[PDB]
Amino acid sequence: VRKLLPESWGFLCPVHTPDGSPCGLLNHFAHKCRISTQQSDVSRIPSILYSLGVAPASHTFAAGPSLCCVQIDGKIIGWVSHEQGKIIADTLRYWKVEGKTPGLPIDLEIGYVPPSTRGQYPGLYLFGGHSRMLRPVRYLPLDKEDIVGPFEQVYMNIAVTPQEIQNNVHTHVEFTPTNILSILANLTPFSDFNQSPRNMYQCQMGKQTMGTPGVALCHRSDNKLYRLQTGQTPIVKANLYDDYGMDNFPNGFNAVVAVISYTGYDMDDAMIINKSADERGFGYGT
Amino acid sequence: KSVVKCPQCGNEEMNYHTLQLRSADEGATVFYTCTSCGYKFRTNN
Amino acid sequence: MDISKPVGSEITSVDFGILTAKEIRNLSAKQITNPTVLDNLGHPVSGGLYDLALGAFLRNLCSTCGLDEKFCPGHQGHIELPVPCYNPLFFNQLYIYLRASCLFCHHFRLKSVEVHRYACKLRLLQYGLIDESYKLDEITSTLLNELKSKRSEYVDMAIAKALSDGRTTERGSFTATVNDERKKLVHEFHKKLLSRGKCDNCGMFSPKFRKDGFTKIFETALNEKQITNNRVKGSTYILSTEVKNILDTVFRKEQCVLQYVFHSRPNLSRKLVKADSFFMDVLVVPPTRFRLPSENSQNQLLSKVLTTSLLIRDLNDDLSKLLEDRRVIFSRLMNAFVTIQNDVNAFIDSTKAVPIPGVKQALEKKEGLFRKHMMGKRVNYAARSVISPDPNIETNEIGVPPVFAVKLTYPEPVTAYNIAELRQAVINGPDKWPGATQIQNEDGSLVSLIGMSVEQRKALANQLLTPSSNVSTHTLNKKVYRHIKNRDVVLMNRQPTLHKASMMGHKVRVLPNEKTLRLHYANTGAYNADFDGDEMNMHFPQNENARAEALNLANTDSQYLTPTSGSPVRGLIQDHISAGVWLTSKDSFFTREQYQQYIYGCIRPEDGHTTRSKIVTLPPTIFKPYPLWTGKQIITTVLLNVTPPDMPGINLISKNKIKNEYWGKGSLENEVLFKDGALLCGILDKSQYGASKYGIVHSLHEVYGPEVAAKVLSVLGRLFTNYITATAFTCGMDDLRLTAEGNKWRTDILKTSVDTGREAAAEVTNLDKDTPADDPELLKRLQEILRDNNKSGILDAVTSSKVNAITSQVVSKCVPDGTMKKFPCNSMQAMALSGAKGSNVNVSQIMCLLGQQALEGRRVPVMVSGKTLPSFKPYETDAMAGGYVKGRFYSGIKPQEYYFHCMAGREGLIDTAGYLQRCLTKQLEGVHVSYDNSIRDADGTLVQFMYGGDAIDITKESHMTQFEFCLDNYYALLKKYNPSALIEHLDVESALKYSKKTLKYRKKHSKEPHYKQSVKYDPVLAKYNPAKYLGSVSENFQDKLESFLDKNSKGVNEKKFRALMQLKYMRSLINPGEAVGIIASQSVGEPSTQMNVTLGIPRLREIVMTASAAIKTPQMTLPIWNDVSDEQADTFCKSISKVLLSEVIDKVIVTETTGARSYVIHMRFFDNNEYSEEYDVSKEELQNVISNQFIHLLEAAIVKEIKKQKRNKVQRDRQSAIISHHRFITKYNFDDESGKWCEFKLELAADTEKLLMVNIVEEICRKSIIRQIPHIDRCVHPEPENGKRVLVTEGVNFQAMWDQEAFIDVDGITSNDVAAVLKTYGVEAARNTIVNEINNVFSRYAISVSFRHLDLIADMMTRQGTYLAFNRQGMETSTSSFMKMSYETTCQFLTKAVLDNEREQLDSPSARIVVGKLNNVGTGSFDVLAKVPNA
Amino acid sequence: SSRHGQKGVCSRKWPTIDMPFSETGIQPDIIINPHAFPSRMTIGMFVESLAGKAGALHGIAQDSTPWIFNEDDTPADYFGEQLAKAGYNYHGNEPMYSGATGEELRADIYVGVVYYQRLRHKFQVRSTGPVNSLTMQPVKGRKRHGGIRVGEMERDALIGHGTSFLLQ
Amino acid sequence: IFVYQNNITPSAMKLVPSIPPATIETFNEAALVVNITHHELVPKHIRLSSDEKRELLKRYRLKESQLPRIQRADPVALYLGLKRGEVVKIIRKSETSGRYASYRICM
Ligand SMILES: [Zn+2]
Ligand SMILES: [Zn+2]
Ligand SMILES: [Zn+2]
């Protein structure tokens, strides 16, 4: 249950997870994974599925995987063939992205499950309720923002960058390959070079820093509060650093760091500081 | 026994993806979307 | 403890007993009666729980002794109970004797002649007469008076025979193995005592009793069927006074039997055992010191006893006043009998009556009293802080801050030699170092120096050394509690202290500025202590006994070789190893100034390091044009000044981790060469100094001693630090690059990897190769692989094996041949080749190729859709899609390559997230080397007759068979043993006479195997004491010496050298007093930290801890003969295999017609040519499974579901016989001409509702065996390990492999299951199966724990001739009561101790910490006796 | 700690005149060991040292959002060419001198600025003090001047050396 | 000794200890197929005389009951036919020392 499953692409962060006992269980969203919070527009979708070929569920006489079942938010709208049920599931994506249809919202989750030998149970499971997980993705015919859920994602092909789009297999592409990482995960620089246990520790040790909590500390009466005195914006920063306003909250300082065995005192994990560095207020906090 | 020629810039590399949109009676719409220059269009039947 | 306040008397033994009621009335101070604790005005009520007679309480004097709170020891009182209540510690055994006894003659119901037999068998077992109790059974109304004479005369005869033949004292002999036969016999006694119908003396019944749990008792209704014997003889809650009114009369008639049941030791006190001993008429309240308020829970439990005790006294007032009132007062008084019982239950046992914690639960578990406050204690004069790394400290020292040097203090008694340095120390005072914080005067006074000025403090410096003013203190002197100086000793200690080298004795050296403990780098390999904020405990011993042990015995220089393997665990780690690769280069040349600065910067003669009082140097390597000193010549003169003079230099030929191809063309810098102590060639590496065997530090250890070698690591630790602060060491982005040649090599082998994922796809799926990835048949078959976990494992292992071959082609070309900056100038590569930090797989993943990211033996997991990830198409045959990443940490990995690498990164963090060693060390704590060289338990019982068979120390045997090293160092080892100064005390000649009577005998034999050999002789080691007789060595050492000394032939001759290895052996003997059982059990638990059959820590769980007779996966190894072929082996595996009927059937077609339910079970097999080749099942054998085995199981499942739905001539006569045996089969047939099908009709009634009858057939066919050898599932013929032909089966049945003589070597059948080789092959074959299977659990992980530890853990587990576990069920046969009470289930061992009236000699180390004795292992294994000159 | 999972305690605040110094005269205010890098494989710290040093010279920032660099254009080539146009070394190195002996060090030492973080995280002693009321053993607790525990695993380590007066 | 085919009547097992001092031993015919003392994992077991039992107990200063124990029911002390309380000598092969003689007693 603690595993990093492949279905978490763009919804859960790979690195931002603690080490030790909450590992794998406590984990964080991606920074572009927004959560549905209001019931989406549903009442015109059964009207425009009957115009696509779906027989109504009153007088249908069908069951099982030999057909595919059309469900909107948990109720059967009707029955349609596996052939047509992918045809009437590609227009519902084409018409929700090209927003000229007055019944299909952009926030809809059209999860088509294709028929397969001993796979998942087939059907067309439309979802529009509360509390869903949603991520943005760019839809290649008529390039616009499409919003997809995890139940919808596991059967469709997105590309991580438009220089890797392969023809007749890739439907979508991502806006950027960094909307899968969390807040704290984008902010570690050159993270595609570090070993992965060393990216996960910085999500642990970036939020154990004596930084600046806020600026309104006079009107705060918190029982323990760590404030670093002279923070600096980084030279080497991500582009989401400017975007979240992390310059309002400086968590450190640009130190001239030498990689040298000179001292003898700094071997295993330990380091040293220039003595006259923090005679001048280097790393000082209260 | 189970063993038994993009028109704007000019480049042959340009992506495409087809969908059969409304029914099996019509033709699959052949969409085209560029990377070199950025012109996009479609083709039905 | 004060060393000038001795103690005369010591506890010798303890013995467990029960307070009778007469004692605790005479014992008591004042009985207390009202259930209130303290009334108003703050003063406690007199007569209650807090009482001034029970002790001083809150500034108020004791009413018994008249002392205040600081000096009153506390006093016990008692409370009266009006009825004798049960003791919940003894109700489990009272109800045994409450039963099994007739209520008329008040004997037991078992016959008195056989109750006399157990009283005579248990008398002999009180003494050391375990044999004669079995001879007593061979001794067999008038003759029973003479049979009870003959049995009793033999008991009295055998005691006086053994007591006169020096065998058993009148105190009795009580070892472990007579505690076994005693507990077995009393369990035998109590078993058939309870199972009786009538008393065999007065022949009638007695009403049976009922146990409601605790707190109550019930008798049952006597049946009307057997009341008639109660007339020809001429339910009810019974009282606790009615139970005692039987068991008094029972325990009087049968005094001669329970006198020996309730006594382990012979009863020299002649105390009669009573039934009042099982009740408790009078509680004892603890003193008021031990129940002070936090009120306290023991005052709350005693309150409800006293609250009930006044109700039941007032309820008895009406009984003195007296019919309607008599009826109600006695059904309510009897309600108060259960409640005052239920209170004293809940007082003692909180679980036998959310709740208030009782008296038992203050003792039982961890966070209790034995484990939280006796075996482990909070300590004084101790400290704890974070450690930081520190060079320049002399490797046996610790760096203590001034904040530690001021608080911690030591009692120095003043003498003539102290009063110069201890007068100045007492002037400095408490806040100056080196100072003093107190003075303890002669009369036990104590003068604190904190609130004193400098004038008063100098005045007491002259009162310090005065003659004593009193005659009573005329021999004492004042003790100044000085500060800790630089000569003191310290126990450093880091948790978890998994082995004994994690708690070492350091010298001290204060530092004047910084506020943290400081530790040298050669100690981090022992404590497992990286300096990432780790902290560790510092203990300061307070007397000269403990100072002499943390300097000589638990010293950190003594602990160079770990006792796990014998390998060194001390050495330099990261920057010193990288500096010695640069310093011992051929490029290193030093001028006259740079040479002499490096040598003095590490030697410093004024700190006591050199041995010459003048730093001697060498002539330079080059003289002209100007003199220069090579870096080989630094470490030559470094090793020349720390070595003792007039002793020759070391001769050493070793190698290192760096090959000759990294240096150039024709370099010889792989081998190191010390000749005359001079480094003539080679690079000093991790293999030389470090935790590496046979280095130069490990060779300085054997030749020059443990003090000279540990001084080298100080000097080399500073010589490689002063070289670094002038000639530094860096690693940059330049070090991570390949050439444009080397990148082109990388991007050409990695272009092969695109078709690799598809060649591995078509090979697993058994398509023909060169098929496209979008083949509709490849994609059809890859979906079937995904749906099975097993078939996906053989796809994720073939693809993994091919892309890890594309990985190795990149690495074995692009590095070192194609790296841009090269060795030694390349530094990422240098510190990986040198063992400084990193591996070669770490520089591979940076510079070449990051590789197949492996999950739990697999590739990256796949979704339901066949996609591995949203970026890839479903079911693609790409190597990149499975987790094989082509990127590196220098260039960068793609976003889908990064999500795969975060899977394997997370798994290593889940696999990161202590009781095997606890169960081991508690059983083995007292096992020590005796002075017989014969290791044995603390109570005297014997484990091994010699330690490992040779009694040599693991930490003294690393060079014992390094014979060619010692021949190069003959004149250096002869100085450290000095054989000429040892001839006067030892017998040189006699053991060498017997050393040839056995060597010449054994070579003349050994043509035969070991069941024939009448050996005629002990080995020379089990007859002569090897510590005293020279030449008494082990047989392997005698052979390996005489095999070494035979092959090669080289001013030392052939016979001066064998007379030195026989003396190096004798000094390598293990010392008498070594705590072996701890060391053997710290060398198994601590290597378990780094951890088709079970493996690892669950394998050690089954062997050591549980003694699993029902092992999880038993196997058996069958040696194939050298005559039969491999074709006669795999067709022999097919004759030993559980072939189910499920394994032979293609499909079963039922056919159900009704309208008598007609089932037509037509079952279809495979082709007869096909299942007579894969399983060797014949056509006629398959018929006899259906004829007699399948259908009778099928008929017992059709009826079983009906019972629970109520809620030609050879064939037609065969058909009629199957109908005749069975119930509702009307037709039967079988394919005789082809063996392909089988069909049998199956009728029922019509009352039966519809059965499934396919899911029945699917369950009966999986339980129907064609042929089966019992307890054996499958026989596998693997590849031949070690050149021998091995036939592994998946079960244990030794009998049925004895028939297969013609295929299997039956006298070589080894196994895996120890409790089955114990049963068929005896005790000494279970002892070898336990050693070899506790070995291959370490042989897998390349962990080499020596066989001396595995041998004692074997011989401890088989000491009783059985296979005993290391748990509480395997330690019941043990003498030490406090050992078992400190382990677990304390009050179950407490009541088994006190019912047996068990006296213990305080021999185990667990029982010498409960009572505070000195431990009998190591230093307390002998007395020290002073010779006084006059009479 | 850096932003790359590299934490380490302070050993000693090393004096400025005993620190190495470049030809430009700057002296580093953190020394990190070159051995923390191979077993940890935080190569992203090494390219922050190039990008940090090159950006302080030109007065620019650089982005470091991941996957802006292909395998073709290594950032060691993107940030090395910026260090070469400032007069500094392409490989991020700088010539430094010993602070103690004043000598030219062998290799050019790899320096640069990297963003550091100060983390947030002890020292009890006891000679004598208060004891317990039930057992007369030292009190549990740092704030109450109490002692440390010699437990059961510490007990048989003292048996295991055979030292019998240290355990007493 | 008394080798039988399948089973002895449990009331007929009342006679095999019945006559002293003449002991009666009892073995299967299916258990005596392979001699267990020929196995590679068992050592050479030799029972000690009473004059060599005492010299063992004198050298190590032992009681009779402090030795390591062998059962009376394991198949090696049924092979030799050991009566309770006589020491057997075990010539045991080791990995590091070779042969070393150890001893067990049957209780
Ligand atoms: Zn274009
Ligand atoms: Zn008192
Ligand atoms: Zn009776």
Image (cartoon, coloured by chain):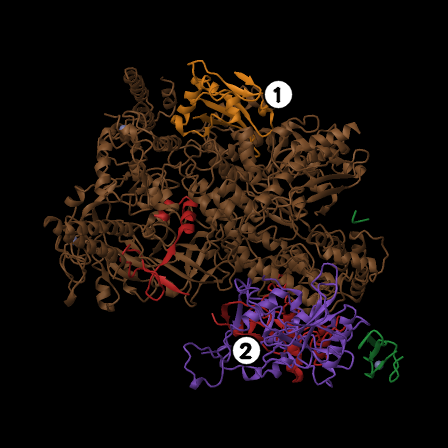
Quarter where residue C46 is shown = bottom left
Quarter where residue C427 is shown: bottom left
Residue at image position (49%, 64%) is C533
Q: Amino acid at mark 1?
A: His
Q: Position of residue C223 (x, y in %)?
A: 32, 35
Mark 1 vs ligand 3: CB below 8 Å: no
Which three-letter amino acid code belongs to the residue tagged 2?
Answer: Gly
Could you tell me how many numbered marks the image carries? Answer: 2
Tags 2 and 1 touching, CB below 8 Å: no
Instruction: Name the quadrant containing residue A45.
Output: bottom right
Q: Write down which chain is painted red.
A: D
| B9 horizontally vs E71: left or right | right
Percent x, y for residue A40? Answer: 63, 80
**Chain identifier matching the brown colour in the rendered picture:** C
Q: Colour of chain A?
A: purple
Chain depicted in orange: E
Residue at the location (49% across, 60% down)?
C392
Q: Which mark is residue C589?
A: none
Q: According to the colouring, which chain is green?
A: B
| Residue under label 2 | A252
| E34 versus B17 height, above or below | above
Estimate the spatial distance between the alpha carbons at disc 2 and disc 1, rounded to whole Å. Answer: 80 Å
Q: Quadrant of the N terminus of chain D?
A: bottom right
Query: Which residue is denoted by mark 1 in the rendering?
Result: C1005
Instruction: Tell me the chain of label 1.
Output: C
Residues behind callouts 2 and 1 on a single chain: no
Horizontal and vertical percent position of residue C398 = 44, 58
Viewer-proximal residue among C1287 and C241:
C241
Residue D72 in the image, given as x and y percentages of width and height: 77, 72
